[PDB]
Image (cartoon, rainbow over all chains, first blue to last red):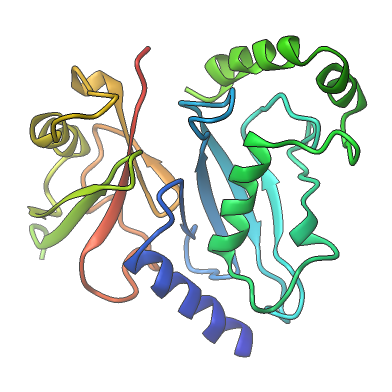
Length: 148
Length: 93
């Protein structure tokens, strides 16, 4: 229970001063299982949206990253039909210096700046590279349908 | 032991919050939202007109109107004890 203690610390800090763009806590009594919401940033087409994320902390946190899936549908190059996220800092840039807050914030940055060259959904990555104005338009729309 | 108190401050899109404010477990979310529309500070690029335009979020869950603070309690919802921060999202529909 270094993991528990550290998770607990991250909760405590988060609850004292949460990032303005996200909210998260444990769902029930399993404290390795949180849920969270990302507020689509103003400086993205996902403005106004509220997106639901689930979080599973592994047993040897913080040496390995948490698992993070979107539950809410999004039109995004790096997030697929099953809410899998392609995010640098859940892969090779994980560090045990990082916290779930820091992770949640990265997901915000991802909404405002996608990486089409590391796609999880090639039609969207292609649309993004090829025809950005249409990507922008398309959620937006999906933000209204599915995140409001 | 059904009507106990907790302190809420409300985090806004801006980064600014308003509160803290004292409420009872018996207070409804619906109530909490009205309080938000009311104390809404001045000079925001956004202003919620009504109650139907504000979503409240606490510990990762979107709180639904007709529930009460007490039923929007999770085992890990306030580890420290003190003020609970809740997030306000203003959606013009």
